[PDB]
Length: 304
Ligand SMILES: CO[C@@H](C(=O)NC1Cc2ccccc2C1)[C@H](O)[C@@H](O)[C@H](O)/C=C/C(C)(C)C
Ligand SMILES: [Mn+2]
Ligand SMILES: [Mn+2]
Ligand code: NA
Image (cartoon, rainbow, N blue to C red):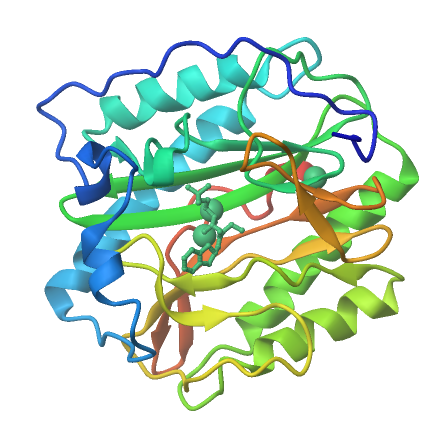
């Protein structure tokens, strides 16, 4: 393997962390290949669930608890902290909230959250690497509570970062928010990609094509697919009651990705930095409710 930049995996990984049996588990948690039979039964389809009132309540709660756990991780971002140590704290924080860490064993993913540094686009595996001053790191949290998943991420600065890092991070956040601002009933899912690319391109950045936002509720990934690039052919039209994520990955160089030999970590083929933000949204009559918003602070962590 020829690495595309300066990052390398830092092994060994800690043995798989157990989740106490009193915590309710999703179907794939005990499948040997981490396959989800409830998602596989729906691979056929592009039909979107209209959430019941009970489902909405279940989504509001798991997304609020997922925000709480992202904020714990945000608190830990400084030089010299390993991404495994951030994962360990996330794992205890989910169990404290009587939730299962949705990524753990999902398709045999080995950890409880994803930590993506610098040229990593997404799905980085927490490992022994201490964070370095100047890094940008994304922490991607998903919890499962009472049958529902809630998904969100932010990119953070490690100590002082360069001007390029600040611009990439700010533009990525603005891409996400301008796409959120367009959500309301009757808009096509395929439109959000136009909005995101337009703003990335205006700032000289590119949009990852290989990874998309997704419906989420009783399944971790389900309809609709929500691409983040322009002129995509996503199927579907937003209606009140729909829940899904928007999770744009934007890059300093070109948009092309590849995957490390570990089968998970996705990296820019050119080795340049990529940043991401994600929220889980519910469509309402007046636009949408950001289920994974902060309730007690106006801005994402990188602004503070
Ligand atoms: C960018 O990543 C998103 C992602 O793969 N979307 C795709 C849309 C979709 C639709 C159907 C099946 C898989 C997928 C993945 C993903 O949802 C993340 O937000 C999530 O936090 C990480 C999940 C693991 C690492 C546990 C997979
Ligand atoms: Mn996520
Ligand atoms: Mn997601
Ligand atoms: Na990155």
